[PDB]
Each structure stands twice: as C-alpha cells, then as structure tokens.
Image (cartoon, rainbow, N blue to C red):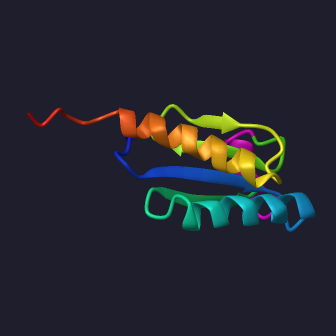
Amino acid sequence: MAPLRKTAVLKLYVAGNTPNSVRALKTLANILEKEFKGVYALKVIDVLKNPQLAEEDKILATPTLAKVLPPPVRRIIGDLSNREKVLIALRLLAEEIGDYKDDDDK
C-alpha cells in the first residue's frame, strides 16, 4: 500500500466480455495509452475468471473504475462508456498526483 509518485495504478473490474466491459476497457485503455501514456499503469481484474479476487475487493458491480495507487483507493462509478467521463476523471486524478510532491528539492 506504498504510495507511488508520478505513475499511478488504475484498476478496472470487468465481468467476462460483455459490451459494457468491452466498451469500458476500450475507452479506458485507449485514453491511458495515448492521453496519459507513461503516467498511468492500467490493471484489469476479471471478476468472473477470478471471483475470489472479486470477493476479496468486494466487487459487486462491473465494470468498476478504481485507482488503487496511490492510496487512498479512488472508486469511480458511472457511465464509463463515455470517453469524456473516463478522460475527465483521469485528468482530475492526475492533477491530484502532480500536486503531491515527495520533496521541495530546494
């Protein structure tokens, strides 16, 4: 649970290959691969394939957007099929990360 500087870890919880999960994954991954390339690390958790992991993180809905790192974990719930919401939410989260500096270095 050690906070990371600059690079943040975003986890997407999906269920199989449903249109909602496919849409959400394409939207989040593409935005992170181009819009936030090199800034965020994307992690995808398949709740149906590994329900044990889903239960461990108490995932009762899919897809679910959550920033596991840096802590606290940011859970974002809404229409992720819309690229604007994914982009806007990622942008706001990134600003928070940039604001937090390890040291002034002066």
User: In the image shown, does 50 or 101 lie closer to the viewer?
Assistant: 101
**Residue 70 at x, y percent in the picture:** 45, 40
Instruction: Reply above or below: 96 against 62.
Output: above
User: Which residue occupies the extreme right position in the image?
Assistant: 19
**Residue in the picture at 47% in, 38% down:** 95
- The reply to whether the magenta stretch includes residue 54 is yes
| Residue at the image position 70 percent from the left and 49 percent from the top | 86
**Dividing the picture into quarters, in which one does residue 17 lie?**
bottom right
Which quadrant, please, contains the C terminus? Answer: top left
Q: Is residue 53 left or right of residue 1?
A: right
Residue 103, percent across and down? 19, 34
* Quadrant of the rendered image containing residue 34: bottom right
Q: Which residues are magenta?
A: 48-58
Q: In the displayed structure, does residue 97 sit left or right of residue 103?
A: right
Q: Residue at x 68, y 53 (%)?
A: 12
Tell me which corner region of the image, top left, top right, bottom left or bottom right, holds residue 1.
top left
Is residue 28 visible in this depiction of the protein? yes
Across and down, in percent, residue 67 comes to: 58, 43
- Work out which residue is located at the far left of the displayed protein and give it: 106
Inspect this view and state whether residue 52 appears: no
